[PDB]
Every structure is written in structure tokens, then in C-alpha cells.
Length: 84
View 1 (cartoon, rainbow, N blue to C red):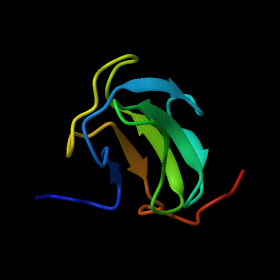
View 2 (cartoon, one colour):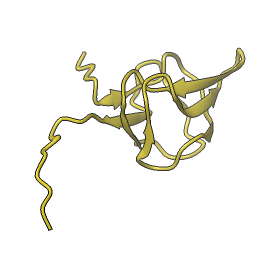
View 3 (tube, rainbow, N blue to C red):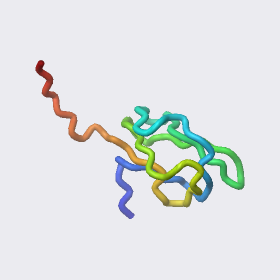
């Protein structure tokens, strides 16, 4: 329902096989952020846009079609204020 761009969800029910990036791993659109070994075959999860991926579920947890496996830190508050 609330499919926001700053989020991530598995396409189908599977299982967290491993991870290609730690919590908040900066990855651009198309870049894999994790993986999920389903009863069918092995696959890699990637982001739909540029941003920092934040793991939500725990390692080994079973993925579900629609469940949020992670998140996305989109450049929303891209404030340009640097002065030191």
C-alpha cells in the first residue's frame, strides 16, 4: 500500500541468505544491497534509486512477498550548509 521510494521490500517470499552491504550501506540505483535464497533459486536484492540502505529485518529471517526487508535513505533533507 504505502510503497515509498525511501524503503525496500522483497519481491516474493524467501529467506535472507546474506548481505552485500552493512547497515546504511551507501548504494546507487541498481546496486545490490543484499541477497535472498528462495526455494526456486538464488537472487540479489538491489535499490530502486540512489541512497543509503538501512537493514530492517534480522539476519537469516525469512523474507515475505511485500514485507520490508530494508529501507532507503533518500537525499530528502539535502541541506547545503557547510561552514567551519
